[PDB]
Image (cartoon, rainbow, N blue to C red; front, side):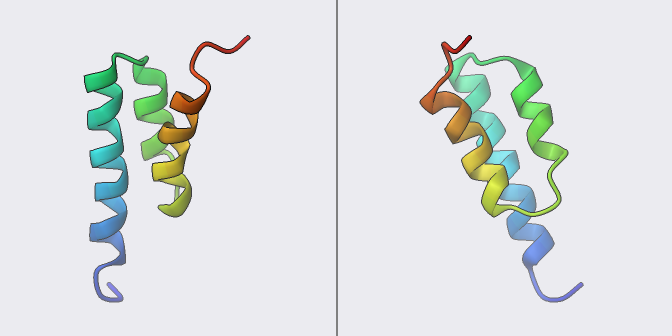
Length: 56
């Protein structure tokens, strides 16, 4: 209730998950996102998982 931090935060993820669905990645990462408290890491979270999807 500061201004619009929660609104923009929900988008970084809400929007970051859309890519996970459009990409085909696992829902694990779509969820692991919503678990975040901030946002800067939320968006980079999935985009980072994509930077190295085929990992060990």
